[PDB]
Image (tube, rainbow over all chains, first blue to last red; front, side, top):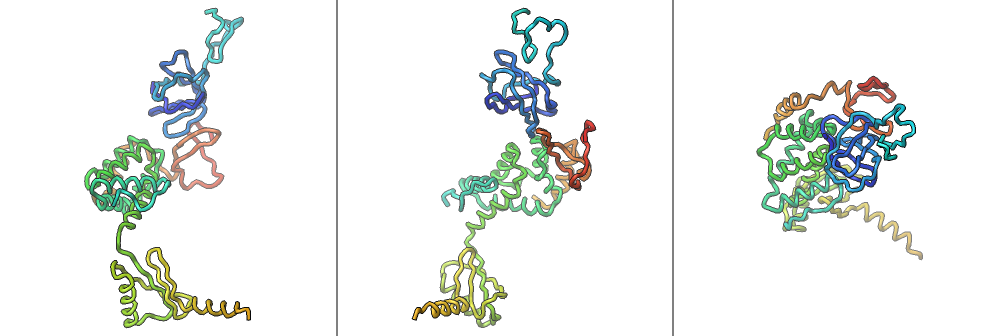
Length: 98
Length: 188
Length: 58
């Protein structure tokens, strides 16, 4: 959790990191949200700041909220288990089938 | 003087220079900050490594603070120290030299001494120059000034004075053109 | 204060930060995005020169 919410502009959210920054296209996860909010890194604006796109509603966010760097882009579950199963953009099941 | 800088500007360097002058001039001191910012100007042009440091933007805030402290923690007015800390936080360290110079401008505006430049075609004789001083002195008679000379005009036997920001034309060339134009528009 | 502080700042510079490599041949990326990178301290580079990044991409 080496990231912080510097600013929040609608769906776009900028995360202030320290030291190493998340590689572009990586998937960041916000901590403290009601539901899992994943942010996809789009570009590095500079000054230890990065611009990301939110995969879920950014309502209820707060500046300085901790953010964790997954280190890799959005990872979705693949395989025969997804067959016959409704999957979300972030790989979460929305069919209430476990 | 009412904690009001000479002029108000929205420029980056202008904003910090104005706030520093007002904040500095507020409590008691203006010359202390003036000498501090002047030191940066001299060092900014004398030390090459110092120039690259300020111009450097990819440097981290914590790194910049450590280097600034190494320079000097004393002999700088608290207003100057607080200013630097603000620039590091706002990544405005690159604009340090402009702020320094801009600040001195306001201070030079408060300075009462002014330089008056006289422009004349014919060489000014030692005795003639003395008479010029009495005219300028008797004209103001309430403010000291320093006189400067520069003789490379196109006019002939004309006098043109530049005093900081004011210009008064006593040149004969202006008289010649004025008459030649009015004599043409007689509409006889 | 003193004018000889350049050596003091230079000393703190070399040790304070594990950076500042050969600027005339190396540079630092200030920002990356929209297919554009803001390299820093890449002095002496020529217009159209071919540069190479860390990962090997040119």
